[PDB]
Amino acid sequence: EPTPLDRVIPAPASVEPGGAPYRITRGTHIRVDDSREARRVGDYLADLLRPATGYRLPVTSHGHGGIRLRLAEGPYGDEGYRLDSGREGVTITARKAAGLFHGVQTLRQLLPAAVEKDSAQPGPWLVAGGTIEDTPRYAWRSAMLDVSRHFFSVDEVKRYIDRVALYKYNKLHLHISDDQGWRLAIDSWPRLATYGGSTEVGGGPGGHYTKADYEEIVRYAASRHLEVVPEIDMPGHTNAALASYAELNCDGVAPPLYTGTKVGFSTLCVDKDVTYDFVDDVLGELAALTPGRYLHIGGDEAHSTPQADFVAFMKRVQPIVAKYGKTVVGWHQLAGAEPVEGALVQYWGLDRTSDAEKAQVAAAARNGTGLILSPADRTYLDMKYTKDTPLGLSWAGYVEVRRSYDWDPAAYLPGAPAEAVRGVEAPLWTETLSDPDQLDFMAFPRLPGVAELGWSPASTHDWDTYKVRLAGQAPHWEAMGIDYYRSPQVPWT
Image 1 (cartoon, rainbow, N blue to C red):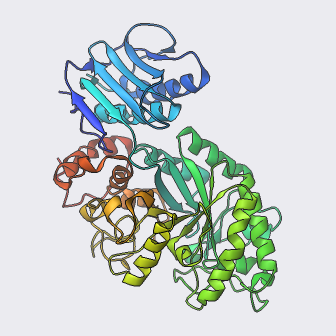
Image 2: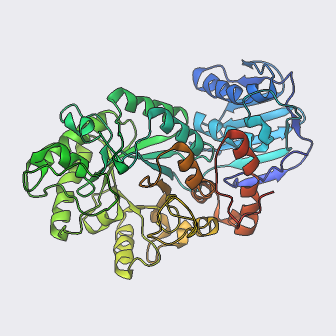
Image 3: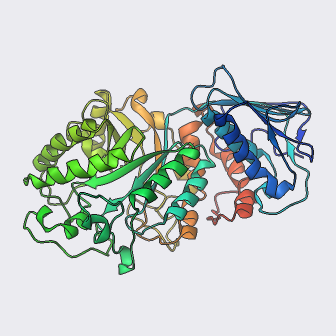
């Protein structure tokens, strides 16, 4: 029996099951349009299927049937697709390559779990019959990775990119500086990466990306249809920079490198002009490496920080983003600091966040500031599932699988108009996480849920049926080598 057509995450916008399934066989081919955009997705698909099927699966621009990837006019937008499956073949149609790529991600979930293995497996290889028509609810569907607290290599970042690409995320937010590390070479301030990147939480060896390493991350991300959104957090969470350049400190003394896990103690010197020269330089070199539309300038503070100083810092820094041709993104503290036109704010509050803090973000939303939702008690993937989780944190409460999923972005933040909501983000902080398996353990199984909230229509939202689709992913995760938390709330087979 093929996996039912609707058993995919994100839930597709429209699923119409019917007819006989397609059978992938030794004669199956991949037919693409005659072009580069085209062959690239076809070659990606072949690379996914050839190992486990053992079939040749040539990519061509001729031949009836097989798996057809077609670019055509239709109601697909920039990211959407239609997927038709029947005895004669499977056709994925889209307007753009991203749409074809998203359709491929659906197709792999429709196939048996064994398709993800790296050597030949027995068939059969059925794709349920019918039609999926699918376009995203929100344009902002992002995953963050903190490479500051613990450092992850280029290859490890590539591996994470491959995890989030499964679920049709379209942005990768890279938290590339914090108190415990600075992870990008800045030629004008070379000690940042070399000294400020020398360690990490726990005092081990750190690391940093050369400019070439960063561009490679960006290129790989783009090949998986992820726009990279880099963050340089400021004015707070700057100890690594402050430790590298004595002159950045209000007292002229470089603090020691920090290898603990406390937050809120560090700040750039808001009243020294060298601070703005530093910010201008860093964001300039970062913008030149960033083909995407956004720079995330953070917006964490120190406990010390007077609101007046935070406001002045942000009034001066935001224009620098536009100077280099990019759009501002900031954590929701920015909502109290006059966000410039077109800035986005990322809301990380929790239920126990004060009514007044909630209303100030809502007020900004009513004034045209777009909102990215990533509540710390909903989509922070570093939050423990329960009191017994060995890694992660619990400052925002425990966050089991249902809580993470069961909400509606459009009816979430009191006071905020639904049309301000741009999408959602699932941040993975790494105070407690030092290896890729640990990232997987805390990312799965919640990561697909947040993807669903970004992509799927509200009409498909339902925990009791979602949890059955999520349990259906586990055999795939097992074949792919993805560690995960076997939540007792999910009905694993």
